[PDB]
Image: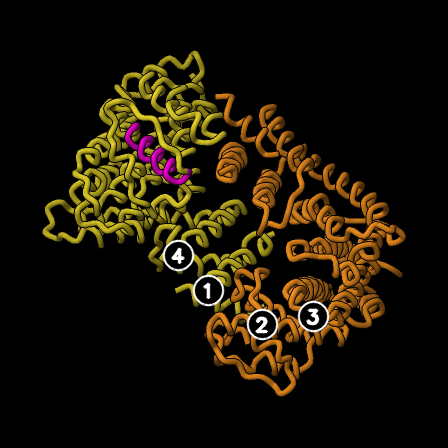
Chain colours: A orange, B yellow
Amino acid sequence: DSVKEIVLPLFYDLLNAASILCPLLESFITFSETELKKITDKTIKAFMDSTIGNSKVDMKYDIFAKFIHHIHHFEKKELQEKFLNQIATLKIHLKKFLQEKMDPNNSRDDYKDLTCSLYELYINKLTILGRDYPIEVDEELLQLFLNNFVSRIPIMFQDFDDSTAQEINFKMLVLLATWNLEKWREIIEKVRDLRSVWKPIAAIIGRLNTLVISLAATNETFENINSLFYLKWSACTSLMDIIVAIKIFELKLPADATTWRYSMSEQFPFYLHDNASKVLLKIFLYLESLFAKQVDVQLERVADEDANLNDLPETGFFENIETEFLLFTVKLKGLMKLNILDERFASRVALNKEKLGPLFKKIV
Amino acid sequence: DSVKEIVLPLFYDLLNAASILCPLLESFITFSETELKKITDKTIKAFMDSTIGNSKVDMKYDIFAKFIHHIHHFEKKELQEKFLNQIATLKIHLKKFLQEKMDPNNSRDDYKDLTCSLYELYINKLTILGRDYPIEVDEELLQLFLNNFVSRIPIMFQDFDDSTAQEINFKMLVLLATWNLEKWREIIEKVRDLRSVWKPIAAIIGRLNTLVISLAATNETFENINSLFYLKWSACTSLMDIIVAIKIFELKLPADATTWRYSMSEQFPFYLHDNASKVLLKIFLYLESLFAKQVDVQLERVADEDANLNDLPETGFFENIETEFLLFTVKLKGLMKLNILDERFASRVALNKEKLGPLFKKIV
């Protein structure tokens, strides 16, 4: 029921936010299928016309996310087609932006403003759409994103402030990989029976491994430390999510897909590089310490842990530290159970299991 | 996709609330269509075992609300039947509750604890279910609720604390009335072309007018004033929502539906009693003055207006006053456009329209 499930919730979201989307709210405040087409068109136009920040900072992100989600569930052919049109447009514009504005030959130095535009105009919008709609990107575009942006974060990073770092995340890469696995699942389930099937996913995992490793080699300062740990965590989390996905995809392959299973070990010599694994543990340790400070618990530590960790600075980047610490632990448990992590890593995770509450204890 | 739309969101919601719902999260912390009916059974069990408070105070309310919503949208016949059984069961136990514990013949005096049980065990859960599932109640149950609880709030009111007041709402009544209109609308629509079809809707509107009037006659104290205005606001908003729903049903009748148009004029003498309309205006006035304090403007008033409005205590009942004020006004504009409110009321609503920021001005 479009009025109960789409139009009214939008109207209430807008009303609550106002106390770009003014002409939308303005429109509702007059009047008294052809109708729905016109509200949806106006809303889609605001979405495409706006800059959308990180949800922690911009109420527009969740307003559009909920609306697009409800539209999707309404399952009306003409509306699905409109959103697929928008995803196509966003990718055309993103490709141009990366080629021109983030060209490594460019002398322009303004990494903080470029990174902001990248996310506010393109990456946040496609990340919202890709929750419900399939998103796919050609090799050219994926390569531009990985080379012109992702690989360059650690040199751009000296220019960032905290709110720019906060915008950066890699959920779009996770989404791209999970939709790609999903396309293959169908082909493999109902093909049954190859050189570069894995190329885009292997490119993404390859790049996240290297980014994690380079961020760890960046010098920590009082000024950059919170944002640097946020970026590490962000890249570690997305990398974990992609590994788990691929691994699970693999477990859901039929016994007679033996060519498929071979091509994966052929094309993924590792999922997690050992040096990236070191940074995973460091981030587990960071969140452990933040969580412990929060609950006034004194942690045990193996001899050689960063003494940074004993009085970390306070951080605006993690608002629910418990959820995040727990969420990160649960993902590390995934990897343990798939044998991606070394037993030494398993031991350290469990070291403080008596001290951090009964939920953490159960997880381990 | 059940795991993507139902199971994972439930797991994350639990996880995030954990930082009687332990045994659910615990199941998730262990393992890796038959499984879905099973999770639905375990979650229904927890839902039925729990006491569910007001959403601002109890995280279980939104947790179960979202799970139930996702289950309904999945539209599997066997899952729908589980929730219809739960609705039938709640109704039976609510009828028993009202007969036994809230019988006016009863010597028990503990109305605050009884009203809490009423909402925590029965009313909150049927309200959650009624968002997606048709809730309908027979005459006996409706009369028990209206006689044994609703019409008695003004005398129970002296025993209440703030957290008990905050728990009372009349949403289930609005939902009862709107499901009833949906049912007529469908029949009118599919069949085409009445002596007591309006009886339950009329009973509800009947009772909400009397309650609003009775609450207005209740003596205010420094102690009870926040909770009193809250109950009055709560009854007024439920009443306005029902009136608007009925009016919209009327307006949507086919012009050859003469027997239908006649039955509404004839079984609805009035929608809003004059004495109840006085209370609507007092509540607009209350919300207007809370908003004005918030923004530090001095309001213009009518010559005889209650100066008390100038010196209102702060309230925890409305922690987004601006939105609440704007929402109440939107509903008033609706009743104005249906010709339920008179020019005096309309003039007063507009009095301070130059002073309360651009959105109120635009609405007015």
Q: Amino acid at mark 3?
A: Glu
Binning the other alpha carbons within 10 Å of mark 2 as few (below 14), some (14 to 19) or many (20 upward) gives some
Callout 3: chain:
A
Q: Is the residue under label 4 in contact with that under label 1 (CB below 8 Å)? A: no
Q: Amino acid at mark 4?
A: Phe
Do the residues at pointers 3 and 2 share their chain? yes
Find disc 2 in the rendering and name its residue: A312
Mark 3 → mark 1, Cα distance in angstroms:
33 Å
Instruction: Label 2: state its secondary structure.
Output: loop
Find disc 4 in the rendering and name its residue: B47
Q: Is residue B81 visible?
A: yes
Binning the other alpha carbons within 10 Å of mark 1 as few (below 14), some (14 to 19) or many (20 upward) gives some
Mark 3 → mark 4, Cα distance in angstroms:
48 Å
Image: B75 above or below B301 = below
Instruction: Label 3: state its secondary structure.
Output: loop
- Per the rendered image, the range of residues in magenta is B281-295
Task: Locate residue A146 relative to residue A234 in the image: left or right.
Answer: right
Instruction: Label 4: state its secondary structure.
Output: helix
Q: Is the residue under label 1 in contact with that under label 3 (CB below 8 Å)? A: no
Find disc 1 in the rendering and name its residue: B18
Callout 4: chain:
B
Callout 1: chain:
B
Q: Nearer the viewer, mark 1 or mark 4?
A: 1
Image: B170 above or below B300 = below
Task: Locate residue A242 relative to residue B84 in the image: left or right.
Answer: right
